[PDB]
Amino acid sequence: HMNFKMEHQNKRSPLHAAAEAGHVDICHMLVQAGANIDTCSEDQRTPLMEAAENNHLEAVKYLIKAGALVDPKDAEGSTCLHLAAKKGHYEVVQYLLSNGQMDVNCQDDGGWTPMIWATEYKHVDLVKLLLSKGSDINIRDNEENICLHWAAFSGCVDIAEILLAAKCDLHAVNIHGDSPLHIAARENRYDCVVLFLSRDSDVTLKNKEGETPLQCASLNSQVWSALQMSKALQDS
Image 1 (cartoon, rainbow, N blue to C red):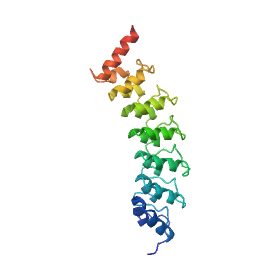
Image 2: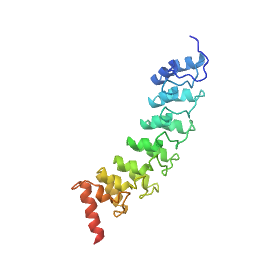
Image 3: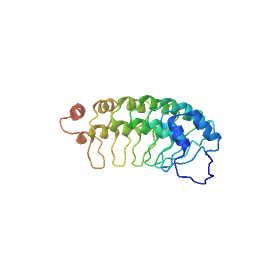
Image 4: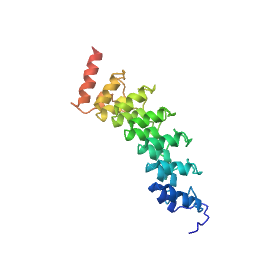
């Protein structure tokens, strides 16, 4: 078949289905026969986003070593980088970084960077990787949260340990004036609230409601216990 020349096509193409399948040859045949390697689907997605998100490394490379644009954004501002990382695909994220020469700090619509995405889905090795390749731990999403806050909200200590070992501010506070410890308490993330207290997080720090992390924990929670034990140990 023939390919219409289009300015801004907004319809899924066969190239999309082929990229998503990870079928390199069919991709090539299509590219070769004139298919636009960067066509957008109804929901504004490129064949590269499709290959990336489905962990199809060889298809990713083909598309890239073919001129595929690496910076277009999703309907919600996500790049193939956000998508692959959000799915925890190490290799694809690796390539998208080196040969891909893509930005580790691009933020989607809600302000989230790839590291924040990899943190939401507790992909430890991925945050390691993203760090070792330039992630700005100080990036603030659209509500003032930095990566530590979500690491706290989620509960993944391994990622939070790592974000700290990276000189991340233990007292950074979001729009509500919540610190990592404030969140780790509200969400009852024990191991987390412990790592934090072990790093001298201010237990007396109030937020914009005047609550201290101890006042945010639920009563008689593993966390509440550990946070008061702590207050008492200080007061004395």
